[PDB]
Amino acid sequence: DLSALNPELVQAVQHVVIGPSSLIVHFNEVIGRGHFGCVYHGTLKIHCAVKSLNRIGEVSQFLTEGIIMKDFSHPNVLSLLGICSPLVVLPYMKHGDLRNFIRNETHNPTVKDLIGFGLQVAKGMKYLASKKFVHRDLAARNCMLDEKFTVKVADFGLARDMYDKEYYSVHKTGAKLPVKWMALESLQTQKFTTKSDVWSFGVLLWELMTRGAPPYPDVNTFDITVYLLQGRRLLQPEYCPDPLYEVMLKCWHPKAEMRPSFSELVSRISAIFSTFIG
Ligand SMILES: COc1ccc2c(OCc3nnc4ccc(-c5ccccc5)nn34)ccnc2c1
């Protein structure tokens, strides 16, 4: 129903919609499980990941969401190939999510590699933030790697889901929130900003430098606000450089407006990264 869309967006429908004859989808093996649906191998011949929304609004809104997301193009942001319940068609990310990749006893990223994964995330977020887009759920689980180990910020738009339900807690609005990645003010208000994405990014850097350790494991869910207000932050991982820890502390500034922009994070991290060999 093209009449129900913003007249500005009608021309973009032909570029976001995938005709079912162009897409093969392999429902025989699940590759990813989200709360809203499963993910499967797909051949579009380009390799893709096809996300079902089986488990789950306005069809017009679903399309506008897809049109917004398809226009996003950055090497460190997961693209939308198109839509085909509607199926979400995404580039295939061979090496899965960042957290599982750094936890994997196969592959041996160096400290330089790990900082580089962080830098890539920062550049993806710099792009997203320049598009005035707030991610709300930045974490290592929610970023992915392709065949060339290019890290991409994912889990947004039509790809948004809870892909690891363990790290989401019920608030009172029944919202299921990633409390251990959330900024102080967001835990209090449930409002998310680019500056709260910056807090989440600091936690992500910590994940990278610990190779995917769970943050605050001896804290129980929403008692995190209490824990933080005692004057606490995540401790410096053994292999995390001093200046990288200083960056994390800046990301966790009590005053949202004093946290660094993603541009500044790209600048600071590029510098630290350049000091390393191998
Ligand atoms: C080789 O195996 C896969 C599996 C799922 C994929 C995929 O699912 C959609 C998606 N979009 N954004 C995100 C962010 C995080 C996760 C995720 C999935 C499982 C476990 C943990 C996290 N999926 N995810 C997209 C593209 N490539 C994929 C490749």
Image (tube, grey):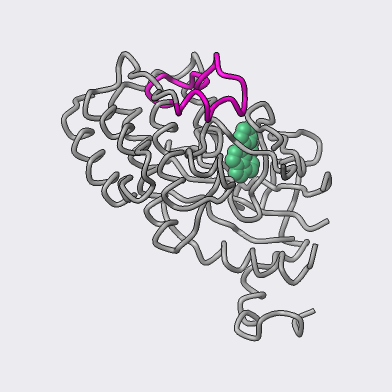
Q: Which residue extends farthest left?
A: 275
Q: Residue at x 74, y 66 (%)?
A: 19
Depth order, front residue of 93/212: 212
Residue 57 vs residue 170: left or right?
A: right
Residue 189 vs residue 120: left or right?
A: right
Q: Quadrant of ligand 1?
A: top right
Which residues fall within the magenta stretch?
207-229
Residue 90 vs residue 268: left or right?
A: right
Q: Residue at x 75, y 81 (%)?
A: 2
Where residue 242 sits: x, y (%)? 22, 23
Where residue 101 sits: x, y (%)? 50, 26
Where residue 227 sits: x, y (%)? 49, 23
Examine the structure image and report whether residue 115 is included in the region drawn in magenta: no
Where residue 37 sits: x, y (%)? 77, 42
Q: Quadrant of the N terminus?
A: bottom right
Examine the structure image and report whether residue 212 is included in the region drawn in magenta: yes
How many numbered marks have been drawn onto this rendered protein structure? 0
Q: Quadrant of the C terminus?
A: top left
Q: Residue at x 46, y 23 (%)?
A: 102
Depth order, front residue of 250/96: 250
Above or below 263: residue 239: above
Quadrant for residue 232, please give it. Answer: top left
Q: Residue at x 69, y 39 (%)?
A: 176
Residue 263 vs residue 156: left or right?
A: left
Above or below 116: residue 265: below
